[PDB]
Image (tube, rainbow, N blue to C red):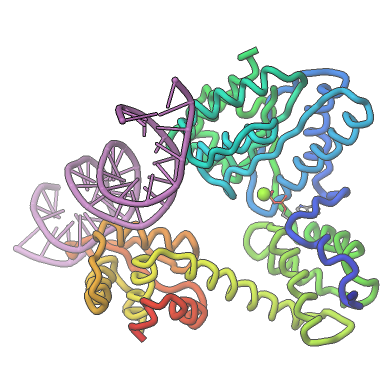
Length: 382
DNA sequence: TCTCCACAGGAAACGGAGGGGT
DNA sequence: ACCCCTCCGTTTCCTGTGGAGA
Ligand SMILES: Nc1ncnc2c1ncn2[C@@H]1O[C@H](COP(=O)(O)OP(=O)(O)O)[C@@H](O)[C@H]1O
Ligand SMILES: [Mg+2]
């Protein structure tokens, strides 16, 4: 069941950590020279990687980690690497509950007190015997929320209840919501990923392109274009790769032995409409109803005020015979919607006429629509 | 140059539905 | 049986603030 368009689609998929990473050799080499000593060696100095999305932080770390294991497995010095993703499983609890399991512990999914599961960690941990590297990708989330900052700390202290940390995030805006204490070991080595010039994204895809595609089907300069779109903002290779791979996905639909400029634009189109739909589906009821209220007011231009949004929100709820949340919460919900980038909001004074938000819709409207309609409540409001 | 509107947006905590280990 | 958890949308209380009016 092959194609003529792909030879290895999965290589493009969001998990394949490749084995060469163009333009991030130094970040590769440093992390290598900061963890190798556990190989002869032991306890490696703790380290930290701020940077932006699509800079290839995760790619690197996971690679170094693959290799660090590749050697240890050939040498036969126990050296366990564990990967934990703070964002995809979001809370201070789970982040421990996870990091526990890898060394081999039970997943009570709720039971606990973060400390209870922290304890269990250091026990099966300090009953069996080696040196272990934790990688906490995207820990900024961690401190976002309670015991977040506290757990962080513990884990950096873990090493002397008798172990090493690699913290990853995506915002210098974190050197600061470190308690300098926490700050001061969550990164003994400052590993920082400066982003991607276009001809760099160029070169990356180029590479991933021999791996994944058949060797003529990818048109000339299409990759330059993917770069262009991914560079258009801050450099982000996910999106570059996301793009060029959705591009070929879409060619297979339109049944040709080639990708060119079009399938990319149509790629951009498919991606947002699915991102959008995926959110507005996975949105709380009253969250949905606010979104509608915005939809309903941004009819014309008269961008919706926080204020207005509430009252026809109030209208909607009643029109359905439901209780209604607070303005505070409506307000919160707005800011959320804005982060999900399903809306975009300006903060602006009207003089003595108060202070409020102009909210407008950022995403494809009809996208949002069919989304909303699938929920059997909003649907009623036709 | 002060007033005071219409909120923004942080902190806490809740409630009532998932569950613990003694 | 006891008191303890976590979670997630939400409630309560709150303090801050750009600029049109007088
Ligand atoms: N230098 C690179 N060479 C090849 N592929 C890369 C490079 N940097 C990133 N990628 C790819 O782009 C995607 C996003 O990169 P990643 O490192 O996961 O982002 P983040 O910086 O958020 O960890 C990954 O799927 C990865 O395969
Ligand atoms: Mg990542």
